[PDB]
Structures are given as structure tokens and as C-alpha cells.
Image (cartoon, helix red, strand yellow):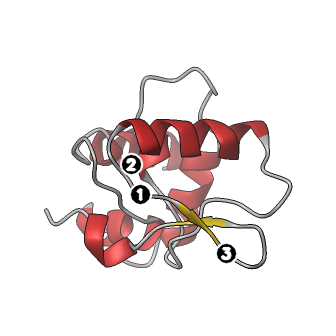
Amino acid sequence: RMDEFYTKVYDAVCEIPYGKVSTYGEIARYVGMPSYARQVGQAMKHLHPETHVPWHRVINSRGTISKRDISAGEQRQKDRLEEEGVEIYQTSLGEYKLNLPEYMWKP
């Protein structure tokens, strides 16, 4: 079932508007599969780095997008979010973060 589920997840992510963000949990509830948040996370993790899907708009519930060691992907996500007007700050732990309620997408 995952093959079709992944495409449903990507369709949902493609709907997050420019400058807004969402989370695995929100998307799962949005596509009518409230208990599949981890599956959503899996779908997102299996995406090709050059995909057209705007994966950078999906962040964890805590509003963070990295851990001090910022991977290439995390750097890409930060770069892309900032380009869409998202204000990103750095925590005392070295993680990049943003005010979730301020950018959270509302279907």
C-alpha cells in the first residue's frame, strides 16, 4: 500500500504554500491517515534529493530543522526556507529553528 501512500503524501506536500510549512503529523491527518505520521516521515525520507516536491516545507513539530552538524540536506532546507521569507534563528544547542505557529500551513 505504501507505493500509493507515498504519492498521496507527495501530493499533499506539493500543496503547502510558498512561505509556509507543515509536519509529518499534520500531513498525515490532512490526507486522512491520522495514524500514519511515521509512514509520512518514511515517504519524505525516501525522496530523491533532486525531487520537485517541496520537502523543505516539512519540518518537525518542535520547529527545528537541524542539529549542530548541519547536514547538506539541513543546509539546503535552511537555504530554501529563508528564500521563501521564513525567519530562522539558532538555538543554544546549535539547531536552526523557527516559530512554527507563525508559518504553520492551515489547509
Between residue 50 and residue 72, name the one nearer to us: 72
Q: Position of residue 87 (x, y in %)?
A: 41, 57
Q: Which residue type carries mark 2?
A: Val
Between residue 66 and residue 54, name the one nearer to us: 66
Q: Secondary structure at mark 2?
A: helix
Marks 3 and 2 in Cβ contact (< 8 Å) = no
Q: Position of residue 80 (x, y in %)?
A: 48, 36
Residue lying furthest right: 69
Numbered label attached to residue 87: 1
Marks 1 and 2 in Cβ contact (< 8 Å) = no
The part of the image, by quadrant, that contains residue 93 is bottom right
Marks 1 and 3 in Cβ contact (< 8 Å) = no
Camera sees residue 34: yes
Q: Quadrant of the C terminus?
A: bottom left
Residue count near mark 3 (Cα–Cα under 10 Å), binned few <14, some 14–19, many ≥20? few
Give the residue number, with chain letter if any, for mark 2: 9
Q: Secondary structure at mark 1?
A: loop
Q: Is residue 14 left or right of residue 1?
A: left
Q: Which residue type carries mark 3?
A: Thr
Give the residue number, with chain letter if any, for mark 3: 91
Q: Is residue 106 above or below residue 76?
A: below
Residue at left 29%, top 48%?
Answer: 12
Q: Is residue 6 left or right of residue 34?
A: right
Q: Position of residue 71 (x, y in %)?
A: 79, 45
Give the Cα distance between marks 3 and 2.
30 Å
